Amino acid sequence: KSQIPRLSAINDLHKIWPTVEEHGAAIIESFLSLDIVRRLNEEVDPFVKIEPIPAAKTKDHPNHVLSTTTRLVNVLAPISKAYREDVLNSKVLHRICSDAFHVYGDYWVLMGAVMELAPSNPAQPLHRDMRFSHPIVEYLKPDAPATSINFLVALSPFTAENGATHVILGSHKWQNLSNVSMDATVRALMNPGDALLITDSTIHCGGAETTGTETRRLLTITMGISQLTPLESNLAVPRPVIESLTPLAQRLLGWASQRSAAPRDIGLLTIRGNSIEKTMNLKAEQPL
Amino acid sequence: KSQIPRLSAINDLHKIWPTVEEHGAAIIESFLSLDIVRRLNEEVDPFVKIEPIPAAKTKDHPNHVLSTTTRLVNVLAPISKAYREDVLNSKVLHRICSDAFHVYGDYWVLMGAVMELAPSNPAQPLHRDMRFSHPIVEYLKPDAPATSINFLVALSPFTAENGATHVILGSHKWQNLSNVSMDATVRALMNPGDALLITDSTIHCGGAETTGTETRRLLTITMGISQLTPLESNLAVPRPVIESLTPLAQRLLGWASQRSAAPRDIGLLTIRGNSIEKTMNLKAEQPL
Ligand SMILES: COc1ccc(C[C@H]2C(=O)Nc3ccccc3C(=O)N2C)cc1
Ligand SMILES: COc1ccc(C[C@H]2C(=O)Nc3ccccc3C(=O)N2C)cc1
Ligand SMILES: O=C(O)CCC(=O)C(=O)O
Ligand SMILES: O=C(O)CCC(=O)C(=O)O
Ligand code: NI
Ligand code: NI
Image (cartoon, rainbow over all chains, first blue to last red; front, side):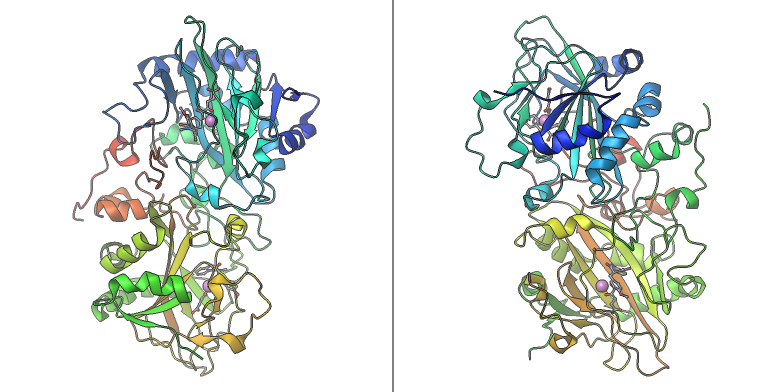
């Protein structure tokens, strides 16, 4: 059977979204440079080491779904200069997202998280994303363009034996889910900096860590239309951090008003006809 | 033909949502007391007098749809004690919204606005709400439960001659929109404090002001599932105002995390497994 299409972030930029739209998945080789991966890893390191189990009893909003051997840390902007500067302003990411979401309008970050899987982390069941947070998405017509997409960026090697993600190609177009089987999957074998791009309808799962020694880490960036509420909030991010960002990054984090693609769009998160950023006199690109 | 069903806010509470679900519209008599209407009117008065045309050239997010004789002012919490206290904690509103949105989960305010129509304001074309802000809603399956509803609360008399709202009963279930005609409408004749309740699929329009003397005013409260982004932002509302609110009102204004109805819900606007309100040590019901 056919493998996940592989594309250049440098040369094949216009081909990436059409490839995902057709096949449900694509690998973007060198989506992030090794320099960015390195800085990103350094910056998030301590925060993933301190992270408790997904369903820690201390938590207000425990995640009862992820395995106990998963450490997920979101709201990365205050943690990581590399994230808030380099990845939030990624030319490749923005071309793909504008290609993907043009029918709907503005898009933003639903969740940017670093996920680290401990050695011996088990395979997840095959699933579609968004079903534990956005029940609305299940009620969309089958030809509705994808309302969110997920960049699964390797921050360490993804191998068959260490739990590289499985996808079922074409499954983003499936309505009958009885052919759902691990027999139908292929793997996203990836180097650090490569990214697996899927839609919210692509059937996929984390793989089984079978070595007992390897710790796999990824940066998962769920980008979605600005009409859907983010899984994560940047409301508590300090204003000096927000004001150091580009206007585009501020929009991505919910620190700007948003626009739909309707011809006479009336906007989202507006304040009596004016934007958040105008109203609050929000500055941009102020060095820290 | 049949008129809009009329219901008591006091006695018929459990019947209101079932009535709207069936007919697409209902009138809730005395939804707000005359005392609340009075205080609300006093408090918003100056702000509607200062409001420029919907598409004022000074505006970041001009509304090119509403007539030039419309004054709409949203983000009412900092303007009105009556709004932020009495209407945001309305027992009737919350019973209806929990009835309406239980399949999806938490709901919040998409927009709370005072609309005032000048004398001679023309009839709006027949329409469904949400199409200039949430293109996603058009892609929902026809049996998808309503994802937003709109309380059109009379703040002055609604009469046939002064432009009382038109609705087409049953039109929330229409898929073919070729029977759309003013011939198919009935009017929401209402006293101050009464409310017309419609869904996002109910076909309706503002009426023609034919007297040349009467100024009609309403409070429009679009309540929607917390998975959809509000038309308006409360990000710039001062913290002392927010901290004077009940926890429920804070949630309604986007100053709290939110939950979906998925069995193992992972939540919306969360911060690494904890809520906004826990993270920011947000107080509630602190008198000003
Ligand atoms: C163990 O079995 C699972 C079943 C389903 C899921 C889906 C997933 C989701 O819908 N969104 C994301 C996206 C990025 C990172 C994590 C998640 C996340 O928490 N869940 C639950 C995860 C695990
Ligand atoms: C003049 O013709 C019109 C055509 C359509 C509309 C729809 C409406 C909407 O979708 N949502 C609301 C809801 C509450 C108050 C105002 C509005 C608002 O601005 N529009 C555009 C209004 C006017
Ligand atoms: O671990 C992976 O590679 C996939 C994780 C995933 O799909 C999820 O948690 O939603
Ligand atoms: O003026 C009215 O009564 C209805 C207004 C309305 O439906 C709208 O502006 O969306
Ligand atoms: Ni997943
Ligand atoms: Ni309307």
